[PDB]
Image (cartoon, helix red, strand yellow):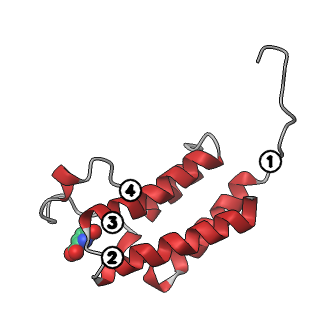
Amino acid sequence: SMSVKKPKRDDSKDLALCSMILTEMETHEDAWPFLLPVNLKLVPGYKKVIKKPMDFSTIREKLSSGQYPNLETFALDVRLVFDNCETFNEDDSDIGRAGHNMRKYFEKKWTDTFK
Ligand SMILES: O=C(O)c1cccc(O)n1
């Protein structure tokens, strides 16, 4: 509170570290469903059902243009990709499995890099 500050964690390397984690997600072989925005004109249901679409290339653009205020807003967008994937796919499908795989892969890199 006012004039009572918690010790300052070091956030100076966060942009580079998030960028690195994103590069690793972009090059994972199961990334293919998540590389580009879903085409809302062509894919049935998606525009109406998925209220906040998100994909790796949109995350890359936001990161490169200073649109993430901190590392937690970055993690929120990444998780949003996989939450959208669960909403729109059966676990027992290739895209459904890719989502579960990529989430596990991300959360491990996140823990290892920051926690
Ligand atoms: O063909 C599908 O199953 C599909 C298409 C677009 C997005 C998505 O999540 N799934």
Q: Is disc 3 surrounded by few (<14), some (14 to 19) or many (20+) residues within 10 Å?
A: some
Please give the residue where the numbered disc 3 appears in the rendered image.
86
Marks 4/1: CA distance? Answer: 26 Å
Question: In the drawing, does residue 88 fall left or right of residue 19?
Answer: left
Mark 4 highlights which residue? 54
Under circle 1, the secondary element is: loop
- SS at mark 3 in the image: helix
| Dot 1 amino acid type | Ser
Residue at image coords 26%, 70%:
89
Distance from disc 1 to disc 3, alpha carbons, whole Å, reads 33 Å
Residue 37 is at least partly visible in this image:
no
- Which residue is painted at 47% across and 78% down in the image? 101
Mark 1, ligand 1, within 8 Å: the answer is no
Q: Earlier in the sequence, mark 3 or mark 4?
A: 4
Is there a contact, CB below 8 Å, between mark 2 and mark 3? Answer: yes
Mark 3 or 4: the one toward you: 3
Q: Residue furthest top?
A: 2
Q: Where does label 1 land, which residue?
A: 12
**Residue contact at pointers 4 and 1, CB within 8 angstroms:** no
Q: Nearer the viewer, mark 2 or mark 1?
A: 2
Q: In the image, which disc is placed on residue 96?
A: 2
Q: Secondary structure at mark 4?
A: loop
